[PDB]
Image (spheres, coloured by chain):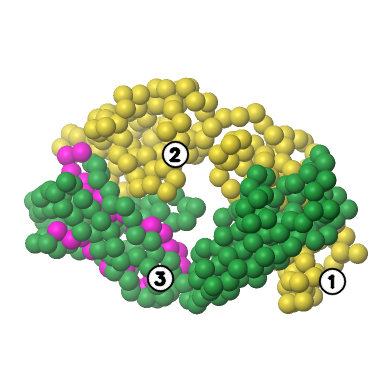
Chain colours: A green, B yellow
């Protein structure tokens, strides 16, 4: 019966002004404080601010970060908490959660809403095969790789031999380098299969309809 | 200005074992009303945070009885009295009655395994990339443990700082290890200016740095 559902996430412009909403149900919205917390990609969950109940007068509180830039509000009559975020920036990319605080703390959280703050437009990825040299690396095993750089937005799907090479694969989390993402993937095969066999990494970037297949070649 | 300190940042555990995470404050966080609003939240990978305990020792509904909270004033403690696979996640203590209101840096509960040296690999830029005027040298360091490791890059002997981007995986779902990728990106010009590129890894599994290198030619 108790429900909190965020909405309003999406892409935003640096210096923009997005606004999130957290609708609730199943409880008396007036009797609760409401928290807004965000978890940036790879970073730790952080607390942004809160708004107080009716009794304590709907007074809000914010962190020193969102201070001056964000503002909590609520629709007491409809049961919708809002998070108006202005002067947006890249650092504001996270998943936003709303929660109600009361006699049992933040016992109900929303499910989250994702925001990405970029000045980038859809960009197709460059795919480069990473081949070894004078040494493969590992006891009779060889590690090959595929660099997937310069794309936007996430994600990309990297596969080895169309899904055959499933074991010995590591796809590392994308990193930002001047608005675009870069990702790399590695695979370890016995020295017997390469280079005698063929090893190909398949990279699909749906947002730009690309699907590149790169043959790893010595 | 109640400065919080939660420890440890990371916690290695073997399933079945006991864990204890602590949250301590420079000053007492007892409220004027007598109550202590110290909470413990559990955020798993890709899930919303879940409340475990509220008001220092009150276990929220649904939370197993193996989870225990304690303390008062300035030092508090969460204590998983029998860790289970389903508890692996990031743990945060929280209090919002005193400025600065906040979550602790977190305590990530990871699975304990035997140490293992990283398998390191270095890769020169592809001819492809260079045809486009850019050169990224890549270094893989997979399957080590503990996660603690430092990578250094050297070009013709000198260490290089700027232009590096690293990324780590999360503990592997099957062998409890971690992997890392270090990429040095330079202009085709810089790359053709130097010949020796070294990727040097430092890890507790050895006093000697693991070095991987290649000469452009």
- Have a look at marks 2 and 3 and say if they share a chain: no
Residue highlighted by disc 3? A11
For disc 1, the chain is B
Which residue sits at x=82%, y=41%? A140
Q: Nearer the viewer, residue A54 or B213?
A: B213
* In the depicted structure, whether residue B169 falls above or below residue A77: above
Task: Say if residue A66 shows up in the picture.
Answer: yes
Q: Quadrant of residue A116?
A: bottom left
* In the depicted structure, whether residue A161 falls above or below residue B40: below
Asked whether the beta carbons under mark 2 and mark 3 sit within 8 Å of each other, the answer is no
Cα gap from disc 1 to disc 2, whole angstroms: 46 Å
Q: Nearer the viewer, mark 1 or mark 2?
A: 2
Q: Nearer the viewer, residue A34 or B139?
A: B139
Which residue sits at x=42%, y=48%? B46
Residue B193: mark in rendering: 1
Magenta segment range?
A79-104
- Have a look at marks 3 and 1 and say if they share a chain: no
Q: Position of residue B213 (x, y in %)?
A: 83, 54
- Mark 3 secondary-structure assignment: strand
- Have a look at marks 1 and 2 and say if they share a chain: yes
| Residue B195 drawn in magenta | no
Residue highlighted by disc 2? B89
Q: Position of residue B113 (x, y in %)?
A: 61, 29
Q: Is residue A27 left or right of residue B168?
A: left
Cα gap from disc 2 to disc 3, whole angstroms: 28 Å
Q: Is residue B115 left or right of residue A40?
A: right
For disc 2, the chain is B
**How busy is the neighbourhood of tag 2: few (under 14 within 10 Å), some, or many (20 plus)?**
some
* In the depicted structure, whether residue A37 falls above or below residue B26: below
């Amino acid at each position: 019966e108790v429900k909190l559902v965020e909405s309003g996430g999406g892409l935003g412009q640096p210096g923009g002004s997005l606004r999130l909403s957290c609708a609730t149900s199943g409880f008396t919205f007036t009797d609760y404080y409401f928290n807004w917390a965000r978890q940036p990609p790879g970073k730790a969950l952080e607390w942004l601010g809160f708004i107080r109940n009716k009794a304590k007068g709907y007074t809000t509180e914010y962190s020193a970060s969102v201070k001056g830039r964000f503002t909590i509000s609520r629709d007491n009559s409809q049961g919708i908490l809002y998070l108006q975020m202005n002067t947006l920036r890249a650092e504001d990319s996270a998943t936003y959660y709303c929660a109600r605080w009361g006699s049992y703390a933040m016992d109900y959280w929303g499910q989250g809403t994702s925001v990405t703050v970029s000045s980038a437009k859809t960009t197709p990825p460059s795919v480069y095969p990473l081949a070894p040299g004078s040494a493969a690396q590992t006891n009779s095993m060889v590690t090959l790789g595929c660099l997937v750089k310069g794309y936007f937005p996430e994600p990309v799907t990297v596969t080895w031999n169309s899904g055959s090479l499933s074991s010995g694969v590591h796809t590392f989390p994308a990193v930002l380098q001047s608005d675009l993402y870069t990702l790399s993937s590695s695979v370890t095969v016995p020295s017997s299969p390469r280079p005698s066999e063929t090893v190909t990494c398949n990279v699909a970037h749906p947002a730009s309809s690309t699907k590149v297949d790169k043959k790893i070649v010595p | 200005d109640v400065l919080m300190t939660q420890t440890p940042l990371s916690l290695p555990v073997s399933l079945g074992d006991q864990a204890s995470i602590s949250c301590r404050f420079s000053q007492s966080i007892v409220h004027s009303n007598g109550n202590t609003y110290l909470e413990w939240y559990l955020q798993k990978s890709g899930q919303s945070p879940k409340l475990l305990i509220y008001k220092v020792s009150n276990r929220f509904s649904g939370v197993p009885d193996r989870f225990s909270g304690s303390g008062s004033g300035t030092d508090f403690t969460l204590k998983i009295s029998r860790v289970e696979a389903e508890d692996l996640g990031v743990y945060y203590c929280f209090q919002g009655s005193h400025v600065p209101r906040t979550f602790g840096g977190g305590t990530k509960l990871e699975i304990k395994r035997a140490d293992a040296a990283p398998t390191v690999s270095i890769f020169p830029p592809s001819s492809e990339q260079l045809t486009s005027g850019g050169a990224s040298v890549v270094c893989f360091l997979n399957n080590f443990y503990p996660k603690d490791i430092n990578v250094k890059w050297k070009i013709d002997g000198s260490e290089r700082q700027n232009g590096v981007l690293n990324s780590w995986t999360d503990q592997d779902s099957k062998d409890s290890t971690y992997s890392m990728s270090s990429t040095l990106t330079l202009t085709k010009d810089e790359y053709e200016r130097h010949n020796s590129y070294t990727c040097e890894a430092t890890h507790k599994t050895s006093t000697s740095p693991i070095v991987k290198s290649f000469n452009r030619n």
